[PDB]
Image: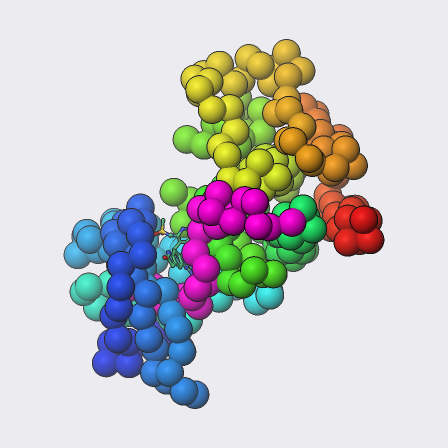
Amino acid sequence: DYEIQRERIELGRCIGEGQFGDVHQGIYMSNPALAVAIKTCKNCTSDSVREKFLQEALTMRQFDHPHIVKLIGVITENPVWIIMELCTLGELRSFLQVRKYSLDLASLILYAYQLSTALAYLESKRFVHRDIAARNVLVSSNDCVKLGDFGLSLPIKWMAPESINFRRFTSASDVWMFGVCMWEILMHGVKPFQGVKNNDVIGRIENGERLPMPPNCPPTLYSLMTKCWAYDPSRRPRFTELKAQLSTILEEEKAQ
Ligand SMILES: CN(c1ncccc1CNc1ccnc(Nc2ccc3c(c2)CC(=O)N3)n1)S(C)(=O)=O
């Protein structure tokens, strides 16, 4: 029973604007009072809007992983809300931009590794995400990030060529996106292909061009990104190998 009684929720501060409405921080008093994120939905009086909004809760219900945000519950009477576990430090991109000169390279590699464990878990369940990007990752603590959006908010600059050309989204296309996400992390939250028009990305990729090696990115990590960006989907690694390779890279950086 994921249905939460509204009297147990104490709506707090607005922390952002989601695709469906404002997102707030709050308190859920079950177990002692716990920190929660509350997604709201401006137009959920409409059944069509409500179904799309609440699909993220139906999807998240299925998962249990240390690096995937937990669904606490839903309130399906107007105003409709989705209650999730709060990642108190917020969005990964802003976190990386603000903490750029204080975070060590070991921390950036650790974030890529933790995301790879969540994605290996989703791969083990045959779940295809379709929207892997640093904008969908949240920060729980200085040493913990979580995949935090399954709403499906066109992200051309992150998409695998087969996704752009044929609308095909598979486990291999998620690996291409994860490569872009790793580039974003190592770039301290800079977006891929800044200044380039969406319809021109396609052409550069076809021409064999890829995102350049971020400054101070270990060459082993960049080589791993280039493997995620094989044009042929069948040539991209799976998450079991990405996770193992990232663990080695992380330990090599920790040793210095
Ligand atoms: C930012 N938003 C998001 N972006 C990406 C993914 C998910 C969310 C909102 N959902 C969740 C779920 C769990 N924890 C948090 N934590 C949090 C998110 C912002 C912030 C603080 C915590 C503290 C703060 O200042 N900002 N948010 S958004 C654009 O509004 O949908």
Q: Which of 234 and 120 is in front in this view?
A: 120
Residue 89 x/y as whole percent: 45, 59
User: From where the camera sits, is residue 195 visible?
Assistant: yes
Q: Which of 151 and 181 is in front in this view?
A: 181
- Colour mapping used in the image: rainbow
Q: Quadrant of residue 180?
A: top right
Give the quarter of the figure containing the N terminus. Answer: bottom left
Tell me which residue sits at (77%, 48%) in the image.
253
Residue 241 x/y as whole percent: 78, 46
Residue 178 x/y as whole percent: 61, 40
Q: Residue furthest front?
A: 101
Tell me which residue sits at (61%, 25%) in the image.
211
8 with respect to 160 (left or right): left
Residue 146 is a magenta residue: no
Q: Which residue lies furthest to the bottom in this view?
A: 31
Vertical arrangement, residue 253 with respect to residue 189, above or below: below
